[PDB]
Image: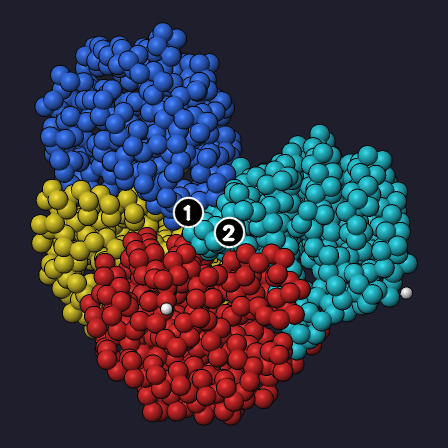
Chain colours: A red, B cyan, C blue, D yellow
């Protein structure tokens, strides 16, 4: 029904990574051959789906774990550059249907900032999408988080370009995988592990002052906010009435509710629940919620049939379906953008 | 207003552990001296609070991390026995106001089963409360989870005695603490880390078949279910429409919704939110929700003023406030139990 | 999808009233020919629909306005008797799938009490369904309400037999129709007028003490309670904090919430909204909510595809879909009643 | 706690009408002496309350039933003019804290249009507030509704001036009162009758095409929309899937949801329920909801302690508390308007 929807947690993979794509599909797809075709296609199948389901514009991003899985920094950087150059060429075929987020190696703040800048200035990319922490160390068992002073140069590039950063999940790896997940491996990914990573990282940015140093910064979480809205009351209470009397206020100057009003966005990717959406409208506000699909891990049909037919007031259907994202991403037109 | 409420996430500590109690208070209390007094008191201050706030009956349990912090199995077992003997003596002073959960060393299934049995048969304890995984290994850096075949003898003791098991959180420790939490330490405890542990463990029990082998088993989570209700739609979708087509069905025979209807309970401890309660009533059902406080980490006043004054239908106020727990714990009377 | 559902706002009309059936259908059906066939059929089409949509048992009642439109008391009573004798014979064809509510002339309390008793004792009817006030007076411009002492003999018959009374709507007529509805006639029926009538009458029963004199009496409203749950807070406030200090307490001894917990039920007829259902769960409680369809004004498909696919915890899906009604109507087994 | 809130269902009475004030207070106040003082005071007590409770600006309007109770058109028009002249002088004492809605005789469209224009152009009033239908006829038993072509000249004046019209309730009178309310009189006012009147009139405006002929017109309902949001699903279904196929489309060209997105607003007057507010956020959207109090029928303390402490995201707290009304009424600065 609604046309001109915007989706922005929508993944692609390079054709040359077929073995890696099949491994990820073995965990998260029930049809590996269709998955390979869909995750690598840009301008045919994806357009056909979008045309059937009222999706005017998609901001595309690299599949997880993507560059965040690559612990050799030279290899990781070369891969990010390769991906960005590739997708820029592909989305030129349909500029009224596609934009792109930058894919980044996050081993080094300045390097990541320069590549984001190249993507925005040269190609008109819409922001960055990164799959949680950067794998690092000689065998990839370490993790680089971005919630510290090293990353100020990077966050300032985001605010200067005035583009958002999407904190996407990745799988647990190395010792964390072995200690917590291997004996309950069916919880890896959407059932639990993904949200544990993203919520940790974003709440780390909150409590380490990233949004105080960079109050213009916009961070996006998928999956209706990776559990955080469920605990908005509890986090707020344990911040304002507990931890902020014990030292948290030194590095965290606003409430969790303020950060969701001013800095944080959530999307509907992979979480096609009107009951949960309504609860998020209460705890986060419809102005801060964006439609998204999570293709090809989720189908256009599941996401769009859900959203198009959900019981919702017309004002919020318009905002969540497209108008919030239109404003955030400064889109002056695209296919069906005012339908 | 409502009298005869039951609370059952209510902690005590042994007087001899004053230094340890002060350390935990330094993280989670804004008034260490009052905290020490309240966590060690059983029969004076706690009764005064309950009398003011309409709490008829409290099931008491040992503070976290408690015995789960003790990696020497001989020491841990001796401590559990000591705690159970102690609290049995203390609650004899007010048997119409207090019951107790067993405190257990969870290093060994048979040992834990025998001590639970002793507590139930000798002292009339109401179940077990355990602070997530058992610390183990020479320096306590390993973790023992209970979602595997070793623990069948223990879960069968729970179902034979027909008493529930409360999966309470504990703090992250060792390598997990260093890798994930030390650089964002204000998230330790109620803001995030606690729920990550409990949800992992309980969803591990689900996906490893514990509730299929032990369909009578009742597991309780605090804090409105440690995020799980927020993702009921998403977990259910990623189980029934994804992982159960890839191998999960071999060890997981019912839906996540079935397990919440048949095996899992949530309490309101530390989560005094009518908006979130309403959402949990939708996703879990009021029949499966129990009032609780989380004293002395939370105050009676905060929990009871919230619940007593929350907008709620009378049927569910009665059930959540006491009648659900009255039935689950087979309470035929206690102070104000039918007021 | 759930089997063995119970629906109980399910209408029929006598074959000899085709003209009246067509007049009503001209207001409320988009396919009059199908409507005529469906509202008169009992044992064929209704079973075809119920078999496709998981409805095990239907409690049938007479179409609105039915006997309540008949202001001649002799004609009205004869019609009620005729209808009850008719439907008792029809349900005997397939008693495993159908029960019936009594149809009554409500001109005279004793007369209506005697006919309800005959229906329960002779035919095993499940209660009464009445279309709001009884038209009366020489030209049918008066209306008989049941919220006064003259009706005590009738309400005592309901409680003695221990069967519920379903307060169904009827159209506005006479002077009320001309003054309020004729100039906005598209609001007649489900859009507004029906709920105005039923809510007035039931809240009349509340404020005139019917449920105080007859505390066992069970009253059922369709359409998720005819707006009343929306104003549960506002009614409760304007009773307990206002009118109960000005004289209402003389004739109304409990709160509106008490009456919903003890006396009043709501059904899902004609209101296939999960968002509104959730809100009713909060304001009324799932123990007091019954599935129903409103056939043939609504389709089995709309009601059952909604309910069967609604996001809902399994506990409440079972209660609302059948278990609440199984208990309330003391039902023997019926098709799929324990599926 | 939020400062600079705007309230706009805030009543006053003329000092010379003490007897009428006391009669109304005998129905709707538990402290008549305080009520008399509060409803007549403008500039002292109202400011004391607003200063304590974070209310920066109050748009005042005339008490119900007000001019709508006056069936002599000459007396009614003279009274409306008197009231507007009176309140314009009162608000000039403290214009930073107060504005006013026009009080109108609604016997004649052109007359009411001319008086609304005088109030806006001469006094800077913010719109009109009218207590439902105008009593009329020789004995006041008739009622004038505004949902027809005779009122086009009036609705065009509202859109030309670009000011809203607040449809406030009044009591039932005359034949309607005797037939429906006299025997259940405790339902008169906030418990039920008020909402029945307003919802009828506004849904009359919908179904008679007022918002099609006047698409810019803004209509406001108090009391969270006078039940209408509860039936948003049911009305929409019975319009789009039923009545719109039977003739309603001839006079009603959009959906009920479209009219709530484009034309209709709701306020929180007298309905201090977060659960119901959340439901209205879903069904109507926070962009269309305005804080209000209903003083002096409700207290500042009840309304403001509720709203200031309600669990709500910060985006919507700001919009509902003041920013929606600041935009709708084109407000200059007032006390704490940007606090
Ligand atoms: Mg190949
Ligand atoms: Mg994704
Ligand atoms: Mg000491
Ligand atoms: Mg605790
Ligand atoms: Mg019906
Ligand atoms: Mg008012």
- Reading the image, the residue beneath label 2 is B247
Task: Tell me how far mark 2 sits from mark 1, CA to CA.
Answer: 25 Å
For mark 1, give the secondary structure: loop
Instruction: Mark yes or no: residue D73 visible.
Output: no
To which quarter of the image does residue C12 belong? top left
- Label 2 environment density (alpha carbons within 10 Å; few <14, some 14–19, many ≥20): few
Question: In what quadrant of the picture does the N terminus of chain A appear?
Answer: bottom left
Which residue is located at x 32 percent, y 86 percent? Answer: A124
The quadrant in which residue A325 appears is: bottom left
**SS of the residue at dot 2?**
loop
| Left or right: residue D148 compared with residue C312 | left
Give the side of residue B212 with respect to residue B168, left or right.
Answer: left
Residue C337, how many percent across, how many down?
A: 43, 25
Residue on which disc 1 sits: C311
Q: Position of residue B180 (x, y in %)?
A: 64, 72
Which of the two discs, 2 and 1, sits closer to the camera? 2
Percent across and percent down for residue D142 are: 17, 41
Question: In percent of the image, x 48 and y 40: which residue is there?
Answer: C314
The residue lying toward the viewer, choosing from B310 and A314, is A314
Observer-nearest of C60 and C171: C60
- Tell me: D181 left or right of C183: right
- Asked if the residue at label 1 sits under 8 Å from ligand 2, the reply is no
Q: Quadrant of residue A303?
A: bottom left
- Left or right: residue A277 versus residue B326 is left
In the picture shown, does residue D318 fall above or below D289? below
User: Whole-percent x and y of residue C23?
Assistant: 11, 29
**Viewer-proximal residue among D331 and D73:** D331
For the C terminus of chain A, which image quadrant? bottom left
Q: Is residue C21 above or below residue B50?
A: above
């Amino acid at each position: 029904h609604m046309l001109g929807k915007i989706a922005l947690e929508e993944a692609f993979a390079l054709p040359r990574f077929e073995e890696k794509t099949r491994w990820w599909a073995s965990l998260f797809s029930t049809d590996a051959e269709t998955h390979v075709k869909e995750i690598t296609d840009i301008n045919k199948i994806r357009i056909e789906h979008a045309d059937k389901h009222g999706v005017g514009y998609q901001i595309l991003s690299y599949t997880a774990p993507g560059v965040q899985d690559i612990w050799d920094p030279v290899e990781a950087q070369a891969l990010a550059v390769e991906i960005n150059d590739y997708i820029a060429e592909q989305v030129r075929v349909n500029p009224d249907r596609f934009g792109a987020f930058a894919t980044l190696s996050m081993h080094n703040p300045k390097e990541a900032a320069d590549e984001l800048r190249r993507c925005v200035e040269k190609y008109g990319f819409k922001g960055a999408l990164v799959n949680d922490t950067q794998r690092a160390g000689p065998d990839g068992d370490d993790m680089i988080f971005y919630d510290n002073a090293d990353w100020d140069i990077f966050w300032q590039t985001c605010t200067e370009l005035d583009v958002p950063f999407y904190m996407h999940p990745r799988n647990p790896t190395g010792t964390i995988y072995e200690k917590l997940w291997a004996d309950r491996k069916w919880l890896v990914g959407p059932p639990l592990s993904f949200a544990h990573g993203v919520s940790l990282h974003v709440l780390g940015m909150v409590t380490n002052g990233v949004f105080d140093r960079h109050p213009k910064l916009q961070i996006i979480m998928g999956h209706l906010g990776e559990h955080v809205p469920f605990d908005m009351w509890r986090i707020n209470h344990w911040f304002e009435d507990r931890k902020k009397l014990l030292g948290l206020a030194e590095t965290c100057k606003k409430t969790i509710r303020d950060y969701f009003a001013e800095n944080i966005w959530i999307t509907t990717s992979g979480h096609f629940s009107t009951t949960t959406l309504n609860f998020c409208m209460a705890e986060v506000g419809s102005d801060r919620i964006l439609f998204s699909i999570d293709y090809p891990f989720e189908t256009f049909s599941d996401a769009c049939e859900w959203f198009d037919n959900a019981e919702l007031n017309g004002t919020d259907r318009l905002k969540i379906g497209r108008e919030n994202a239109k404003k955030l991403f400064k889109l002056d037109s695209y296919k069906d953008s005012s339908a």
